[PDB]
Amino acid sequence: EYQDGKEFGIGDLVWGKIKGFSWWPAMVVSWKATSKRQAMSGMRWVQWFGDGKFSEVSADKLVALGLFSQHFNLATFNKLVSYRKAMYHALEKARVRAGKTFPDSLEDQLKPMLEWAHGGFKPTGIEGLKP
Ligand SMILES: CC[C@@H](CO)NCCN[C@@H](CC)CO
Image (cartoon, rainbow, N blue to C red):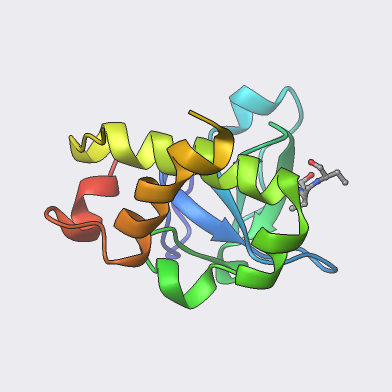
């Protein structure tokens, strides 16, 4: 599955861009997770953080979550609680994968995770976000 010459494999944390939305964090999943169909060549099933829905998205409309500063939308973050919730769930997954720990509102748990992400996911850097 996903042998089409494009990047992103199962478990990869990504930003996904679907028409009419900010870049949104997601995880690349197997089509078997979706209960739908195999993805067309050149596409990936992703599951969006925050709402848990599945979309078939072109691999060219995906970027690594680790490219964080570049794709994080501060306006969307300020405007939408659903986006903030998505960030939390996405960064929590990132955090556990990287072996990272932080020292309790949504915005308060989020604060150091966001700082971590925005700052480059130190000390591991983005290699720590790998599945
Ligand atoms: C319209 C409902 C809102 C709240 O979850 N969706 C947030 C955006 N996430 C969708 C688009 C990336 C994925 O369904």
